[PDB]
Image (cartoon, rainbow over all chains, first blue to last red; front, side):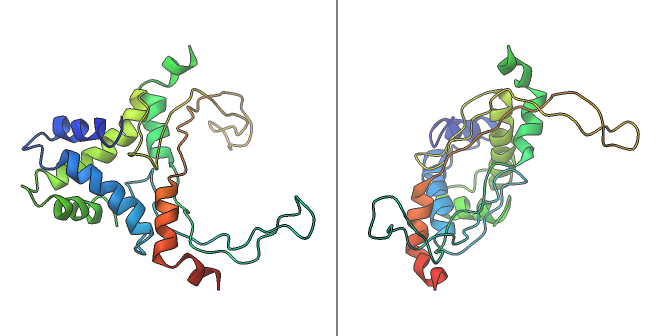
Length: 99
Length: 99
């Protein structure tokens, strides 16, 4: 699925009026990517812990070629996929992917 | 934010009909986690890409005192690094966190 397929995901799980399925998802990244950049820890049930956390602010290796460094972390992306989808996955196409 | 905060995040980015803000987001996580679990490549425009991959895990008993068994049930709900959210993070104050 994606910013469009997901519109159908709500346009079908919901469908009510197709509100902005295309616009709410277009804004979803605008709020997902923008919230972390707005300063808010979005949290999807228990799988997408959207929340920014700094972890880098330098990377110029010494006067050599590959001795890169990094002293100071600036905003980052703490969030990640949780087990809510893996538990849902162990329940629908987990073995389907195995074979 | 969360299954309700992000709701208004789209209910406001939408404001068309507030479709089911409650049913589209509660189901969006139910479909986000359920799609990857259904076995579809869930993703977000160009910053997130949740994808499940048949995998497994084992060596922590359970039916007794837990700490010794040997199974392997664990799909791999991978994901992506939406830089649009990290680059947006540069917008919130990435360096401000580095200092």
